[PDB]
Amino acid sequence: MIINNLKLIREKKKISQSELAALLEVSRQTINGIEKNKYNPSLQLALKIAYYLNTPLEDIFQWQPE
Image (cartoon, rainbow, N blue to C red; front, side):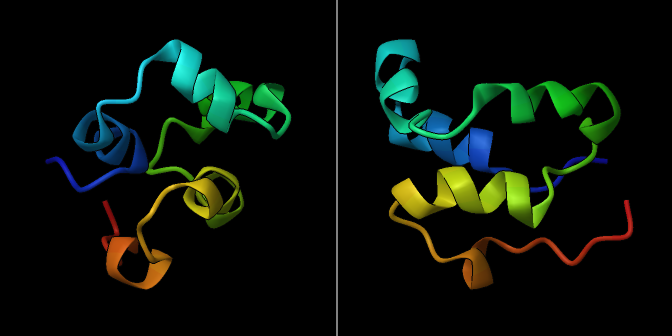
């Protein structure tokens, strides 16, 4: 039903828009893909933020078909 997500990590990190905007050193419009990327964010989507976030993708990776 639900799986771990970097945005949830953001929630865990308690990072607000100003801070997220700080994270957003990558094209935000890429997120706009969420229209169709509403799935758990792709690694490319995840990596850009995950790069900044103190959280390995490996641990983060949700190998869930859902």
